[PDB]
Amino acid sequence: LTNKYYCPEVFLDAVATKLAQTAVLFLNVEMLNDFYVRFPREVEAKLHEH
Amino acid sequence: DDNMMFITKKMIEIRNLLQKVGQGSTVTLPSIVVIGSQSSGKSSVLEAIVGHEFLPKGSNMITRRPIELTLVNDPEAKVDYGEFPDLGLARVTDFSLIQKTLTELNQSVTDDPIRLTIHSPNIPDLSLIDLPGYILKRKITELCDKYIRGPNIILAISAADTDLANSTALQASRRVDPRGERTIGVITKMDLVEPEKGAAILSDRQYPLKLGYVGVISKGNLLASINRNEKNYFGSHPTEFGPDSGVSTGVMTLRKKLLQVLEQQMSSKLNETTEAIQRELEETTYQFKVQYNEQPMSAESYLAASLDDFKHQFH
Amino acid sequence: MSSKLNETTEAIQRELEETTYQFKVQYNEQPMSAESYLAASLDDFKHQFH
Image (cartoon, rainbow over all chains, first blue to last red; front, side):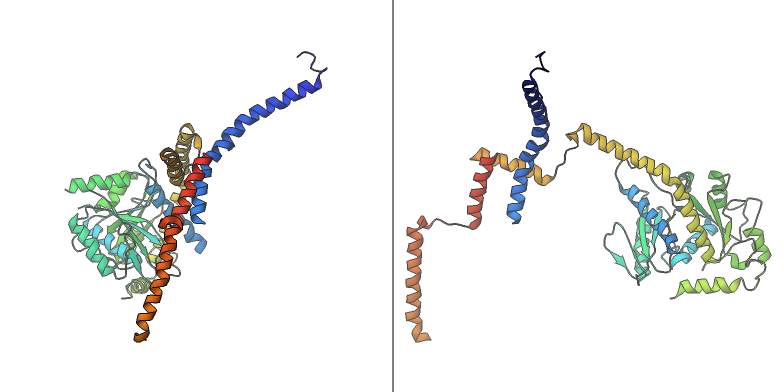
C-alpha cells in the first residue's frame, strides 16, 4: 500500500470504490427504502384515480 | 382607520386559537373582565348591552356562568347576526331568540363560560367577558377574584347614586390592582346627577388610575338612539363635561379607549406568549425526532403498506 | 305492431340464444367485470414488485 504515489491506478480505484460504498449506504436508505414504502401506495392511488 | 381595527381582530383570533390547541395549552392572551356591584352590576349589564346593540340581559340572572363576548368587525356583512360557537353553524337573526336561549342556559345553570360571537357593522371588534357581579355569594367572589387577578384588562362600573368608596367593583379592582394601571372605570346611571356631581365622580384624585374613568348613561334603531341622546345631553351642561373638560364621556370615546388599551396590553403579553408557544412547538418537534426519526406518514401509506403485505401472504 | 310481435319476439330470442352459446363456448360463461380483471392484474404486479 505504501507505494501509493507509485501506483496511482490502484489508489484511485480504491478511492472510487470507498466513496461508492459509503455513498451507497446513504443512497440505499434514503432513496431505495423510500421507494419501497412509497411506490405501492403511489401505484394504488394513481391507478385507482386514473 | 381600518389598519387600526385589524390588528385587534387578528389578535382576538389568536386568543381563540391558543385557547383551542390542546390539553397543555395552559397559555393565553388577555381580554376585558367586567365587574360591578348590585346597583353597579345592573348598570354594567345595561352598558354592555348599550355598547353594540340590545341583547338578552338582566331580568333575573343567576350569573353563575361567565359569558365571553367576541366581536368581529362586519364590513360587507348586512345583518346583525350573532352565533354560538358550540352551537355550530347556527346563526340567530333576532336577539329575542338569543334572549330565550341564553336565558334558558341562565336557568339551566360546571362553571363553564359560554362563548359568543356577534357580527354587526356598527360594533368594533372587542373581546370582553361578563362574570357574575358582586351581591353562594362566597362562591361567586371566589370566581371573580380569580378572574381578575391575572393580567386581564379589568373594566369596573359604578352607579352614581352609590359613592365610590362604597362600590365593591372599584374596591375589588383596587384589591387586585393597587396601582390602578391595568383597570378602567365607568360611571353609570349618570343622567340623574348634577354636572358638578359628574365632575366629582368622572374626575377624582382620591383614587386615581391610569386610563381614567368614563361616565355614560346607558338605557328598533336603539343604537343610534343611545348615541343621539349621549350627543344631546352634554349640551345642557356643555361646559361641565364637554370638549376639553378633563373628563371623558359618551360611548364613542370609551370604545376608542377600550380599543387602544386592548391593543396596547395584548401587544405587551404577545412576546412572552409567543415564546411560550415556541417552547411547545420545540417539544413536539423533538419528540418527532427521537420517535419515528421525523419521517413522514399518512394513514393511506400505512393501509397501502399492510394490504400489499396481506396480498402476497394470501397468494 | 301486435301481429309483428310474435315474429319479432322469436327472432330476438334467436339472436340471444346464439349470444348465450357464444358466452358458453367462449370463456365458459365465466363472469367478468373490468374491476375483477384490474384487481387480479394489480395483485400480480404487487407480488412481483415487492
